[PDB]
């Protein structure tokens, strides 16, 4: 994300990252994020969501 912000000239809007507590809302966001297919990211993004949902459910 940092790299693509660097490429799009939004370097300024990466180090300016804060908290948007609402853990039920965080769970909603994460479960609803779509998964891609063509990119090598297809497995990584889903793995990321799986780990995040398992960790938050444990938490």
Image: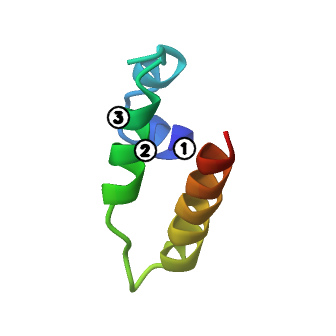
Residue with the mark numbered 2: 27
Would you say the residues marked 3 and 2 are in contact, meaning their CB atoms lie under 8 Å apart?
A: yes
Q: Nearer the viewer, residue 15 or 32?
A: 32
Q: Is residue 29 above or below residue 47?
A: above
Q: Quadrant of the C terminus?
A: top right
Residue found at x 34% / y 58%? 33
**Res 56 label:** none
Quick one: label 1, few (<14), some, or many (20+) residues within 10 Å?
A: few
Residue found at x 48% / y 25%? 14
Give SS at disc 3.
helix
Residue 45 location, x and y as percent?
A: 52, 65
Residue found at x 60% / y 44%? 56
Quick one: label 2, few (<14), some, or many (20+) residues within 10 Å?
A: some
Q: Nearer the viewer, residue 24 or 34?
A: 24
What whole-number distance in Å separates the C-alpha atoms at marks 1 and 3? 27 Å
Residue found at x 43% / y 44%? 27
**Res 25 label:** 3
What whole-number distance in Å separates the C-alpha atoms at marks 3 and 2? 5 Å
Residue with the mark numbered 1: 3
Q: Is residue 10 above or below residue 17?
A: below
Corner quadrant of residue 3: top right
């Amino acid at each position: 994300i940092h790299i693509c912000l660097i490429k799009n000239g939004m370097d300024h809007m990466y180090h300016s990252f804060d908290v948007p507590i609402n853990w039920v809302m965080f769970r909603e966001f994460i479960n609803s994020l779509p998964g891609t297919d063509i990119p090598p990211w297809n497995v990584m993004t889903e793995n990321f969501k799986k780990k995040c949902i398992a960790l938050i459910n444990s938490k």
